[PDB]
Image 1 (cartoon, rainbow over the protein chains, first blue to last red):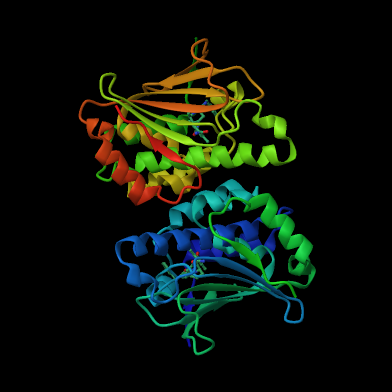
Image 2: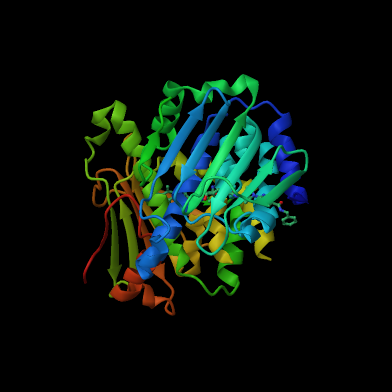
Length: 204
Length: 204
Ligand SMILES: Cc1cc(C(=O)NC2C[C@H]3CC[C@@H](C2)N3c2ccc(C(=O)NCc3ccccc3)cn2)c(C)cc1C(N)=O
Ligand SMILES: Cc1cc(C(=O)N[C@H]2C[C@H]3CC[C@@H](C2)N3c2ccc(C(=O)NCc3ccccc3)cn2)c(C)cc1C(N)=O
């Protein structure tokens, strides 16, 4: 297990998100879904030129998996995934410029999507986030952070995913509404209704 | 015809775009298409609760119209459109915040879309941009700017368009490749292939 400090601007952003009240928290799910759709576009695109890109799974979809007993909500997709270098250095699209711009605006949280840093909105509702991912060019890895300025990265030895990403939200005790069938369905209807990939809720 | 000053940060960004060399200019079309898709999502959403929103036209689509005689490329959609207030005040999601820090990041251009000011990438290729638009709640208007720090807004008495927006790019003399069928086809393929509305490229 390797532990890393966040980029300064990312540490800054995560604290602002965690330590300030924001009403319109439900947008975290829009952001996670939007990320999944983007990752699905990227693998689909690659597969046009080279169909073997889909040897790791042909299906292109997004699954929402609430678990009341674990108090986790997990957003799963069969997108391009992330390599170890992605998990350590962050994605090219997440520049300190997008971050800095956003924080200044903050001081609606929904504008977070605009700036490439939508993932961090998960920390509106979750005390810990685990990201398990498999990119065609790399091994399966787990990235995890409870915020507080650091994250971890390890090779993942669990269940194989073929290709794609699972984002596991370990929810805060006052944010269990996001585990409810009715609530998840209304959020998807309001913010993610025209996403070009099937979104399936795994009812408990 | 009313003439308005640009927001200082928008005026600065437009100067940067016009007066700086950038290589990967084709991304202007991805940005215009993205905006059209977003405008279409918006009217489609409103129609779900109120079918009469589509009295101004039920078809939800995007047209690309090269004109080699006029040296214009026109991006048309049947999306929600913009009101006169939108044309004067700008859109709520275009704010100095996303603008100011993006310029700093510059000093690839493709990062523009992820700061909510993707429209202005049109000035990479166009010496003037005319925007004709019709929203359910307003009259038809023409917005136009050749940059230099100002824009114009007037009623458009011309061809009644139903609902939606036309973005007319009056291309620079050295940017006429964007009128060629093959070039437009290839740009849509690389960047807008999975947009969830029909994109129709007109033949000349
Ligand atoms: C979704 C969409 C968005 C756009 C877009 O970005 N529209 C804009 C509003 C209009 C038309 C083009 C440009 C940006 N516009 C403006 C309008 C006003 C201003 C402005 O600076 N106004 C003065 C101001 C001063 C001080 C503070 C704020 C504004 C700048 N750009 C466009 C052009 C089309 C679509 C579409 N296909 O539906
Ligand atoms: C498209 C997509 C994007 C994301 C996402 O935004 N991923 C990130 C990469 C990983 C996993 C979560 C978070 C942001 N991550 C990181 C990684 C590194 C860092 C970081 O700060 N690293 C140190 C650093 C120091 C100095 C300069 C640059 C980096 C921050 N966030 C995720 C989690 C999933 C998807 C998806 N469904 O495919």
